Image (cartoon, coloured by chain):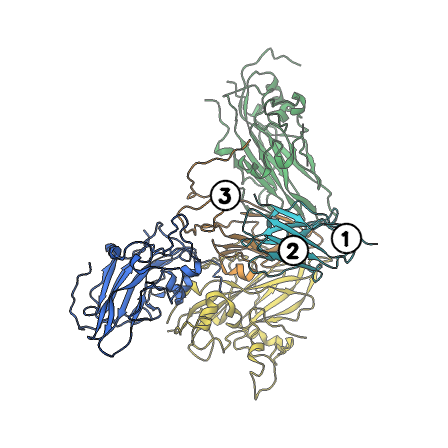
Chain colours: A blue, B yellow, C green, D orange, E cyan
Amino acid sequence: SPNIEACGYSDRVLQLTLGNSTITTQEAANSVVAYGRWPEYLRPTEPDVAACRFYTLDTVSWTKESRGWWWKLPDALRDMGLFGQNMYYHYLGRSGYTVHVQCNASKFHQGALGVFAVPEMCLAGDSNTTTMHTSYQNANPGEKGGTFTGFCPVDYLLGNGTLLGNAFVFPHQIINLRTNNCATLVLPYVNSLSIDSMVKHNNWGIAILPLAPLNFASESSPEIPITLTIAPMCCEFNGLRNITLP
Amino acid sequence: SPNIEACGYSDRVLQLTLGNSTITTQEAANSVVAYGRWPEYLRPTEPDVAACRFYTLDTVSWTKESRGWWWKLPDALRDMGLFGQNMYYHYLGRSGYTVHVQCNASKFHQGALGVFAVPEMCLAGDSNTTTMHTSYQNANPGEKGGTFTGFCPVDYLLGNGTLLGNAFVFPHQIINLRTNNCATLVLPYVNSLSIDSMVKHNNWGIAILPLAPLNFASESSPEIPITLTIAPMCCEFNGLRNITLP
Amino acid sequence: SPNIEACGYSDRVLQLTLGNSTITTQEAANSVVAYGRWPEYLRPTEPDVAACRFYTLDTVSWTKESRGWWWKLPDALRDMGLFGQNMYYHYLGRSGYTVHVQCNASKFHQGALGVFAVPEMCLAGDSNTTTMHTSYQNANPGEKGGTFTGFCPVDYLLGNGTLLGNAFVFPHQIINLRTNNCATLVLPYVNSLSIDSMVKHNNWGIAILPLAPLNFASESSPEIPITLTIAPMCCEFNGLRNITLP
Amino acid sequence: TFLFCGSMMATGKLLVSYAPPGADPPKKRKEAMLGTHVIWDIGLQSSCTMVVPWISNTTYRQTIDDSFTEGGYISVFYQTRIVVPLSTPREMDILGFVSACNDFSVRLLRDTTHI
Amino acid sequence: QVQLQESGGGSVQAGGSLTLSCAASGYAVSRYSMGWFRQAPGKENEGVAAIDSSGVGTTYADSVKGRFTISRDNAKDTVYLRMNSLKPEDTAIYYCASGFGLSLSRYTYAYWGQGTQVTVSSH
């Protein structure tokens, strides 16, 4: 689906400095808007830059054995400064996400990463009658995240009971080592309501699985790191409660 | 100095609702501007209503034995929501104060309170050579405050070695039971610098001592409560540091 | 519902002199129109001032044990000069009522009276199958009236089997000792017909129960009196019968 | 709406507090003080009116006991204390009232009538 | 319907320890706290002890402080009021109530038990 061919190497280093953050993106161009919609305001307190700035999660090692990785939103960013706060001090909250996944290697490494953003991504446990099942804490692995396997999400079953090959229905991009180094996914707020409670309900779900294995030239770096930078877009929350300071 | 005579009873209940707070002042009129200056902005991040709203300290009992009471700014308001936060997250900080001291009694109680705002109010310890002396913690009794005596601040010596009678040089108002029920003192930022560090340096010092004793008709309420509502005015702080969350 | 705050003391003594009567109301302002309707004429003999003037019922003692009091209209005013006459000489009759309930105390007494005007106020006797039940004479206690209890009208059951707290659906005002001294209720004619027979059917029902107990400072007046002044408004009656003089 | 029913002479101040849905019950003045609160003065005005706003996750809330959609808390504390002159009874009462607003609506007609 | 079964009452001796308990039906005991209110013959609604199921933060009345011990069970949905070292003033018909939570106040609760009579019998 993502049959693009920007250039191949590197051209232009154009940094995204929003608020306090700074990114220095590989370029800027080549981004996918989920379903063709930009995160908009409810048609409330709009913090903007205060909440709307780049936060970086923990970097994870990609290896010749890796089966995949997964995170939840806003869940992961629950331990992020002002966005971490505003999440616990309000009963409401809707937010967009600029999932900017970067992965650098050399002209000598080969493989392919597919960043899949699954809206309402519940994980594997074939009890249709009683879903949710796995405890609040397991279902929410924070900023460190969870991982796929060959709480148990099977890779070819996308960790939900449906053949991986059809995953390509959800918004995605393929970080193919020989071409792109970056993945840009703007995910607008998707839920059954106009606004809801962030602490309990998980909107999206970033799942990066390997479509091609990792092969490194003779002897080189045994593993390569993948980084996930996420940012809250056009967010609002109602309404401050006894700023119950922890 | 404060030779006023508004009315005597009660006329108009006009509430001051700033931000999240609500006051319901005895009236509105009869307020003293310290030196004729309003808290202005440095000629920075201006939080306004976020920081600029009414916070109420702990209520203290006035009795026939009371010698007085004293507080420090911003010190007291160091445990007040956003103003408490912004105080520890910034290396700077300048702020004004609307010290609105209320005291209610009946047409049967008699006495007189003089609210004295002493800029740079260091407390008694006659070591001219080595002032400050008393520990950081003693010098800073927070929102519960400190009290005068017949760390030891002598009442007739205003707790600094100068005869109380001359206290009337500092901005003040006299809550005289037979007339006024409220005291309004707007104190603009006063310090040797344009902006400084709030955590270490104490700008003002609210000191309420009794000028007349308390006498209650036969048998009534053995004591009457005095309340201090303080508010940060036209405040600014530079510049967020690793929002070092506690 | 009656969340008003006129002044608190006394301002203006403005007397209501209608016909032969004179009232000298606490003021004039602060009156409740039942449902937003003024007593109007049927859209007949209209006596005006002859029938339309102020009559005062018997004054009753309010005490720390009082459970309440109740009256019926036109019933109470059946022994009132021309309005008493016109009631027995005609087969018809419709009339409005300006129930002006006054209660004076000092700045030292405390409590709260809720004057409730219940249209078609039948009294307690849980025989749904056979209502009315209590004799004509008991149901009609004239100008002396009836009283609630802790013919038996239970106070918390408003004397009809429904929780007092919901009484606030009927037109009312709360004579709260610290604020209002007077209660003004204009009740327009309410019945299933355009005009009916007054002798048999009771339109309204003035019920004054205590919402707060009576507490008097040390030793003072052991009880305080409440007065009910009622007046017929825009009344008409058809048609003189053998002016059957008693 | 809270209506005070004590002596005219009696004075004092109280703090009516509101804590939005999901938040823990404010058990201290300081705690309750931080959130939406009104500082109701007895001495001046006899009646306080605190309009509880629409701070709700779902566009439509459960009238039933649900944690997904749970109300919150309205509590009163002694801002100051009660001051009474002379020998006037030291214990009075306060009444409370509740009502809806123009924006208040309901849906799905159901019943509960027993025999 | 929320039920609180006040169990553990009786006429013991002056200093005689007597525990109390209440079975909390209709709700998750954790969402609520639980306390105790005594009322002496012809007296008033007075507090004794109360704690919140989640925080287990204690609070006693000044007069009862020390001798009385409150403790919650989240498994059996019951509270345990260990009224140890009793006194002739502790002769008051007890009552238990689930709180919103948390502390001994005027009423401040909603679900009330039937009432168990404890009488601190003395020679």
Of A162 and C141, which appears nearest the observer?
A162
- Mark 3 vs mark 2, CA separation in Å: 39 Å
Q: Amino acid at mark 2?
A: Tyr
Picture quadrant of residue A235: bottom left
> Given the current orientation, which residue lies at the most extreme top position?
C242
In three-dimensional space, the C-alpha distance between marks 3 and 1, rounded to whole angstroms, equals 49 Å
Left or right of C6: which side holds B196? left
Q: Residue at x 67, y 14 (%)?
A: C246
As drawn, A177 above or below D9: below
Front residue of B90 and E112: E112
Q: Which residue is mark 2?
A: E80
> Which residue lies under the disc numbered 1?
E12
Answer whether residue B213 is visible to the viewer in this image: yes
Mark 2, secondary structure of its residue: strand
Q: Which residue does the numbered mark 3 point to in the structure image?
A: D99
Q: Amino acid at mark 3?
A: Ser
Mark 2 closeness class: few <14, some 14–19, many ≥20 residues within 10 Å: some
Q: Chain of mark 2?
A: E
